[PDB]
Length: 85
Image 1: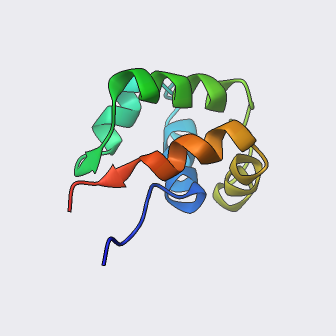
Image 2 (image 1 turned 30 degrees about the horizontal axis):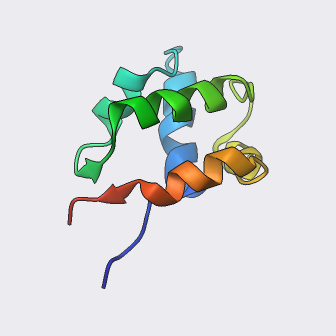
């Protein structure tokens, strides 16, 4: 079928959990949470950098998703992150 890519929904749940446990959003943190996904380390760094400058630490899961959708640069990278399948 070719199921999908890492959506703003899937990413909002990963990030909420990091903010809930007081953890900084790093390349390595995202790499740890994306087992079974195809992702380039340098691309992960750009994704993390873009997320950090949006300052979503205080928001909830469903609102973090909304602010990810509002980012044009983030949506382009997200579509390239696909599962190994």
